Image (cartoon, rainbow, N blue to C red; front, side):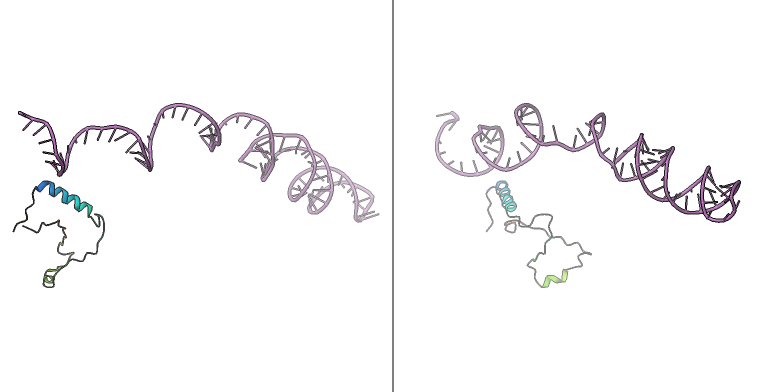
Length: 65
RNA sequence: CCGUCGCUAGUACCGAUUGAAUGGCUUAGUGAGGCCUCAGGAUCUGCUUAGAGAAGGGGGCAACUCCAUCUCAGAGCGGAGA
C-alpha cells in the first residue's frame, strides 16, 4: 500500500515543471486565502503579530507514504 | 560484436522563419545648436534747435521788453541696443 514512484529525480523535476506550469498567483502578491480548517483547532489560533504564523505550500502526493 | 527496435531524459547543431534590441556601412531626405554675416529696432541716452509754463535780475516803467535756471512736449543729427 505504498506509493511506488519509479525514478525520483526525473519525476521530481517533472512535477516541479508541472508546479511552475500551475503557479496561479506568483511571489510578490497579497492573498486572502481560505484554508480548510476545523473548528476545534481554533483554540490554538494565536495573536499573529505575537506568535509567528507561517503558511507553506505542498506538492503532489507528498502526503502519501 | 555491440550492430537493430521503439521509449527515458541530457549534449552539440540548422536558419527557412517571426518578434524585438544593438552596431557597421551605404542611398536619399530632414536637420537642433552656437559662431560669422544681411537685416530689424522693445527700448534708453547724448548734443543742438524750436514751442509752452514757472523763480530772479536789468530796463518804456502802466501793461511791456531783454538775459540767466528748471519742467512739459516737437524736430533733426548721433551712439548703445533686447
